[PDB]
Every structure is written in C-alpha cells, then in structure tokens.
Image (cartoon, rainbow, N blue to C red):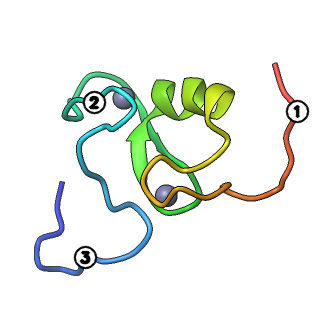
Amino acid sequence: MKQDGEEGTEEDTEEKCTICLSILEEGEDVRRLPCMHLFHQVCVDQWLITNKKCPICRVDIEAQLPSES
Ligand SMILES: [Zn+2]
Ligand SMILES: [Zn+2]
C-alpha cells in the first residue's frame, strides 16, 4: 500500500496480517509495532497481550514499558 518503488524500505512495511494469518484489509484503523512492521491495530493489541515479541522479526519490541488496561 505501496512501496511505489518510492521508496520501500524501513518503518511501515506492511504484509499480510500474520496474527490473523490473513491479508490486511481496508476494514478499520491499523497500527505498527515500533519494531518496524505494520499490522491491524486490533491485532497489535491482542498480540501484545499474548506474544510480547514481534511475530515477523521475532524479538521483544523492547523491554519498555507501558502497563496497561
Ligand atoms: Zn490482523
Ligand atoms: Zn517487527
């Protein structure tokens, strides 16, 4: 959603949602783990609740540091 060529390459790559094991969709608001990778917003949430690590890059997004409910 692109790249367009211009210009890949860094934060906000997207791919298929991987928590939903399904393509992303123009359905609701979306959100990236500050690792880099984008997901559905609702997914980044329920994922954080279960896996405190990025699903793709596999690592803890950081040690930090919200709470929260
Ligand atoms: Zn999802
Ligand atoms: Zn990641």
Up/down of 31 relative to 42, above or below:
below
Element assignment for label 2: loop
Image coords of residue 62 (percent x, y): 74, 59
Is the residue marked by circle 3 packed among few (<14), some (14-19), or many (20+) residues within 10 Å? few
| Residue identifier under label 2 | 21
Image coords of residue 41 (percent x, y): 48, 32
> Do labels 1 and 3 touch, CB within 8 Å?
no
Nearest the viewer among 32 and 63 is 63
The label number, if any, that marks residue 67 in the structure image: 1
The count of marks equals: 3
Q: Alpha-carbon distance for marks 2 and 1? A: 27 Å
Q: Alpha-carbon distance for marks 3 and 2? A: 23 Å
Q: Is residue 37 rendered to the left or right of residue 61?
A: left
| Residue identifier under label 3 | 8
| Mark 3 or mark 2, whichever is nearer to me | 2
Q: Quadrant of ligand 1?
A: top left
Image coords of residue 12 (percent x, y): 39, 61
Residue at the outermost front position: 58
Residue at x-position 56% and y-position 61%: 35
Q: Is mark 1 within 8 Å of ligand 2?
A: no
Precedes in sequence: disc 1 or disc 3: 3
Element assignment for label 1: loop
Precedes in sequence: disc 3 or disc 2: 3
Question: Callout 2, which amino acid?
Answer: Leu
Question: Callout 1, which amino acid?
Answer: Ser
Q: Is residue 66 rendered to the left or right of residue 20?
A: right
Image coords of residue 67 (percent x, y): 88, 32
